[PDB]
Length: 94
Length: 93
Length: 94
Length: 93
Image 1 (cartoon, each protein chain N blue to C red):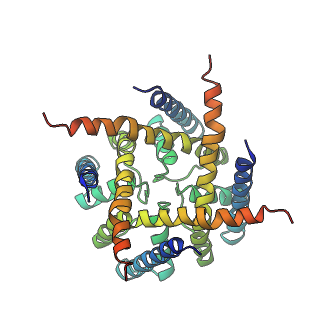
Image 2 (image 1 turned 60 degrees about the horizontal axis):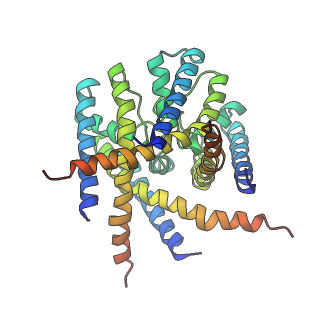
Image 3 (image 1 turned 90 degrees about the horizontal axis):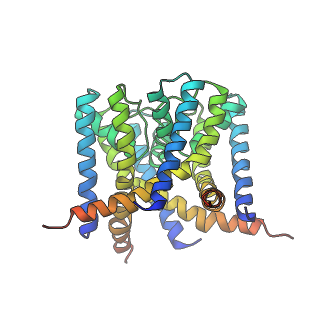
């Protein structure tokens, strides 16, 4: 698998579980929506409203600075170490 | 050009067709809008509302993780291997 | 100045003038707003509504793919070749 | 740590204080909201409305160009020089 990708994967899931728990609890979201927000926020897509609560905004500011690096690193490794080899193997003629 | 840019181009179009098909079918969008969402979502611009359905949100979460890398790699190759040479050639007196 | 940064700067301004002209004309925006959109769109910040018109959406899709690379390259060079030296010079004790 | 991360940290806080002061004063926002906008705007997340005033839009255009590089450089250094070592040390049995 490659221990780095594996670890990046775990950390990213941990980061997303944490956001998911925080947003459903504090912003009153359904888990699906708290997870959805966490994800589109850390990947910087952002096509949702902002948080309503001041805790929500605060946590969110911290969550982005601490979380964006992990998330983008995971994507990088996924693309470089997972997807690129898959594509390679799939462009082989047999 | 080069087979690499060409392939990256095809994959990106495939990824965008797939999103287009998914969003028009599941979120009920006109193809233009499903394509428009796919594109602004994978490039992370996101200037639209979120998906309405739970399938839509689920697929979208997966589509971002799997798709952002391809899309940004394609833009990278386009910039480096297509646009930069074009600008070079067209700065020559 | 450094000819590369200079050229990147010009291209980015050209790209932004083009978007500014397109959006004020086709989406009916005030120039300030057409420029504002162009900018937050190419930098991927996106905190505006989408385009209304189908031409608008089409042009926008093409404008992002062709424009995001230039814009981010310009930012990179600005940060590396302009801002970093300024900061350096400004951390010198005299 | 290292003087570099430290400096990048200070500059980012300075850039965010400046945006905070600007937006609360010119766009009439509570400091929490002016800080919140500054942050999601420079990190490019953007999940809020745009500025209302023309000064606000102008400043914001400039603030993105000048500020995005600092902010992303700081995140880079934080990830590379702070978070990676922390994770390393805490994977040791």
